Image (cartoon, grey):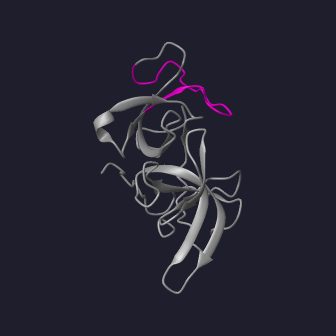
């Protein structure tokens, strides 16, 4: 457990498929450790199959939930503008899978098309859900869409914290 008691990282829930910036408040090992970590708690890995006790800052009412490193990724603090959106590029946006024209839970989208008119910069992308995907959906949220953190290209949140708290 390498994440600290003040480590608010982006916990991608696999079940609903939605990203939520969750606050790591405790790390525990898959070895006998239910309380505050002790007795040589040095347990790193490539993808740590150890239990990060996080709290969705997007839904504080969920309280402390258990998520592993494979589940909790670093929130890449980079808002991608329309002109930086390009074909093949996957980016995370506040998206309602009930209505693409309204915001909701943070999902992925692979940019398929981009066409600006003098009334608005219009975007159409394959919005990637839990394991599913929604090809050619209007991306209204081009002003506030973040990037997916790639191997090397993934910039960490060292600058001003977001902690978007997506819980309408």
* Residue 77 sits above or below residue 70 on the image: below
Looking at the image, which residue is at 52% across and 40% down?
17
Q: Is residue 134 left or right of residue 39?
A: right
Say whether residue 104 is magenta: no
| Position of residue 109 measured from the top left corner of the image (x, y, whole percent) | 59, 55
* Residue 136 sits above or below residue 24 on the image: below
Tell which of 98 and 33 is nearer to you: 98
Q: Quadrant of the N terminus?
A: top right
| Position of residue 40 measured from the top left corner of the image (x, y, whole percent) | 54, 21
Figure label count: 0
| Position of residue 36 measured from the top left corner of the image (x, y, whole percent) | 40, 24
Tell which of 168 and 23 is nearer to you: 168
Looking at the image, which residue is at 49% across and 63% down?
159
**In terms of image quadrants, where is residue 7?**
top left
* Residue 39 sits above or below residue 3 on the image: above
Residue placed farthest to the top in the image?
32
| Position of residue 154 measured from the top left corner of the image (x, y, whole percent) | 64, 55
Tell which of 85 and 165 is nearer to you: 85
Q: Is residue 83 visible?
A: no
Looking at the image, which residue is at 50% across and 33% down?
15
Q: Is residue 112 visible?
A: yes
Residue placed farthest to the bottom in the image?
118
Magenta segment, principal secondary structure?
loop
**In terms of image quadrants, where is residue 69?**
top right
* Residue 167 sits above or below residue 86 on the image: above
Say whether residue 39 is magenta: yes
Looking at the image, which residue is at 33% across and 42% down?
59
Tell which of 38 and 78 is nearer to you: 78
Write down the region rendered in magenta.
35-53
Q: Is residue 161 left or right of residue 128?
A: left
């Amino acid at each position: 457990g390498l994440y600290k008691v003040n480590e608010y990282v982006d916990a991608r829930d696999t079940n609903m498929g939605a990203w939520f910036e969750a606050q790591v408040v405790r790390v525990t090992r898959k070895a006998p450790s239910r309380d505050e970590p002790c007795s040589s708690t040095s347990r790193p890995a490539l993808e740590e199959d150890v239990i990060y006790h996080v709290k969705y800052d997007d839904y504080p009412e969920n309280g402390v939930v258990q998520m592993n490193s494979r589940d909790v990724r670093a929130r890449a603090r980079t808002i991608i503008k329309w002109q930086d959106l390009e074909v093949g590029q996957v980016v995370m946006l506040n998206y309602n899978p009930d209505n693409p024209k309204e915001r909701g839970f943070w999902y992925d989208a692979e940019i398929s098309r981009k066409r600006e008119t003098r009334t608005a910069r219009e975007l159409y992308a394959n919005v990637v859900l839990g394991d599913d995907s929604l090809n050619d959906c209007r991306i209204i949220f081009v002003d506030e869409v973040f990037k997916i953190e790639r191997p090397g290209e993934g910039s960490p949140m060292v600058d001003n914290p977001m902690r978007r708290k997506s819980g309408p």
